[PDB]
Image (tube, helix red, strand yellow):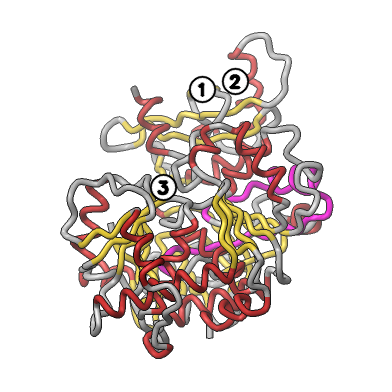
């Protein structure tokens, strides 16, 4: 079914661009053909095997061809971005039980206990098996693994049913039409990319990829953006914020922008507001979910009304085929409006971590016959609406006082003269010593740094208790992002600590 709705475009709109990265692009017809040849090759080489297959690279069109080739042959694929550390890739190879690794580019990771098919060798199978097609019944189905994406060091197994459950909801609730241009910011090793990959493929859209190098060089990023004619924007809030630092990043640069889809981090009320101002015709959606629950399970249309009544934006209503549970600090459920750990239950929940029995036991459970996943996230529900408070382990306790790190960040972000901010907790060694605020200053006329600091501290005093107000402030032109596009908190902690 999933592959069928995708294949449907190879016949209806064969010459439509299915994926484009810089100068490299492939049509739906080419996607089908090479994908079919690979699948045929896989089946000929591994007749009665269904071991997961590693797919190595970055944004090359072959990444997508290889993903489909793998599933058509009944093999789940393991996306491995170039950014993943060698030691990690080696662990994945050994943990996953993979026997093969496919890459369009050169594999730089020191010898892996896997058969490597790369560069020209991959090209050879496309040529060698050109025209051939795989047995329709070999295609991954039902509860069989479709892809395995690693988090933290655990392989989250996402089944066919999991992905279909997500995709259907995404296409319908995000109001995606057909033939639209979908931005792809997230590396394939990050499940945010799934939010644009499959919805685009099933709706005959065009995936417009952006790579790590464009990001390292904004002039190229924006150049690409203007040529893209992107209509559906899928990215982390941080990525959007960085683009917002560019005055030309607006409806003028992307006049056909229609839908913004956010997930992965807190979407600031101010960021959404800036996007509405810059793109008055675009719809903004905030969504929430762990990789363990197939990309996202909640979503909400962030309107002017939502922005007016929710200083802290809610993360959304749970998809209809799943449900949420807010667990009080005890096996007990919490009354609506009360904070607890967010638990997700339903067909979106992963079947567990690959080869990690003990790890699966600790985070996954069975409730009334269905899978449930403890997120490690703190939040609450109010009449179906889910609110995110922060990561349970980011819960800082300052001298006899608890507090979500994210709540302090939320208020810091809301202060005048602040365009971006992150709190770096400085620990004495065991307990929390003090908080350090890293902010990107907005326009101001403060002639001395301490004056800006005092001003923000005064405003923050009206929002938080004195003991939650960061003692130290640091200013910089931008907040670092990890290769996935999220705030790089480790890097920040590393440099501010040094």
- Point out residue 401 in the picture as x, y percentages from the top left corner: 43, 43
Nearer-N-terminus badge (1/3): 3
Horizontal arrangement in the rendering, residue 412 relative to residue 470 (left or right)? right
Query: Is residue 5 shown left or right of residue 47?
Result: right
User: Is residue 276 part of the magenta span, yes or no?
Assistant: yes
Q: Quadrant of the C terminus?
A: top left
**Mark 3 residue element:** helix
Find the distance from the CA under tag 1 to the CA under tag 2. 9 Å
SS type, badge 2: helix
Task: Indicate the quadrant where residue 258 lies.
Answer: bottom right
Label located before the other in sequence (3 or 2)? 3
Q: Position of residue 58 (x, y in %)?
A: 43, 50
Which one is in front in this view, the residue at disc 1 or the one at disc 2? 1
| Image position of 47 (left or right of 345) | left
For the record, the magenta segment spans: 264-293
Residue ID for mark 1: 474
Note whether 264 is above or below 134 in the view shown.
above
Q: Is 3 or 482 nearer to us in this picture?
A: 3
Q: Which residue is mark 2?
A: 453
Say which residue appears at 63% left-offset and 66% top-offset.
299
Disc ID at residue 362: none
Query: Residue under circle 3?
Result: 394
């Amino acid at each position: 079914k999933l592959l069928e709705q995708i294949e449907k475009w190879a016949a209806e709109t064969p010459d439509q661009t299915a994926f484009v990265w810089r100068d490299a692009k492939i049509t739906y017809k080419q996607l089908k053909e090479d994908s079919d040849a690979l699948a045929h090759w896989i089946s000929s080489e591994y007749p009665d095997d269904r071991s997961p297959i590693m797919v190595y690279g970055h944004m090359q069109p072959e990444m997508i061809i290889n993903f489909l080739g793998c599933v058509k042959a009944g093999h789940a694929y393991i996306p491995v971005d170039l950014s993943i550390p060698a030691d990690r890739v080696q662990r994945i190879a050994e943990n996953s039980g993979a026997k093969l690794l496919l890459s369009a580019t050169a594999v730089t990771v020191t010898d892996l206990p896997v058969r490597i098919v790369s560069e020209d060798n991959l090209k050879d199978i496309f040529f060698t098996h050109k025209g051939n097609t795989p047995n329709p019944e070999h295609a991954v189905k039902g509860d069989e693994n479709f892809y395995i994406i690693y988090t933290s060091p655990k392989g989250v197994q996402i089944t066919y049913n999991c992905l279909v459950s997500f995709t259907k909801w995404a296409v319908e609730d995000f109001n995606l039409q057909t033939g639209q241009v979908f931005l792809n910011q997230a590396p394939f090793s990050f499940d945010l990319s799934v939010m644009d990959i499959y919805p685009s493929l099933v709706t005959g859209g065009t995936l417009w990829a952006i790579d790590k190098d464009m990001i390292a060089r904004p002039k190229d990023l924006f150049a690409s953006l203007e040529q893209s004619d992107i209509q559906v924007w899928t990215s982390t809030p941080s990525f959007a914020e960085m683009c917002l630092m560019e005055a030309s990043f607006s409806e003028s640069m992307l006049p056909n922008m229609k839908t913004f889809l956010f997930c992965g981090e807190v979407l600031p009320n101010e960021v959404a507001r800036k996007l509405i101002e810059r793109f008055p015709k675009a719809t903004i959606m905030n969504t929430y979910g762990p990789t363990e629950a197939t990309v996202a399970v909640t979503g909400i249309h962030v309107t002017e009304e939502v922005l007016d009544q929710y200083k802290s934006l809610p993360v959304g209503y749970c998809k209809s085929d799943c449900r949420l549970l807010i667990m009080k600090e005890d096996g007990t459920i919490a009354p609506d409006g009360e904070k607890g750990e967010i638990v997700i239950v339903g067909p979106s929940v992963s079947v567990g971590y690959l080869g990690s029995p003990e790890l699966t036991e600790k985070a996954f459970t069975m409730i009334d016959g269905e899978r449930a996943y403890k997120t490690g996230d703190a939040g609450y529900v109010e009449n179906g609406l889910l609110f995110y408070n922060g990561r349970l382990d980011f819960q800082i306790k300052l001298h006899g006082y608890r507090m979500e790190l994210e709540e302090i960040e939320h208020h810091l972000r809301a202060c005048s003269y602040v365009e971006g901010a992150v709190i770096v907790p400085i620990k004495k060694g065991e307990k929390y010593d003090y908080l350090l605020a890293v902010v990107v200053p907005g326009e101001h006329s403060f002639e001395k740094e301490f004056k800006l600091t005092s001003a923000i501290k005064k405003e923050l005093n009206e929002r938080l208790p004195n003991y939650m107000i960061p003692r130290k402030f640091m200013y910089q032109s931008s907040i670092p992002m990890t290769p996935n596009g999220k705030v790089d908190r480790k890097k920040l902690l590393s440099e501010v600590t040094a």
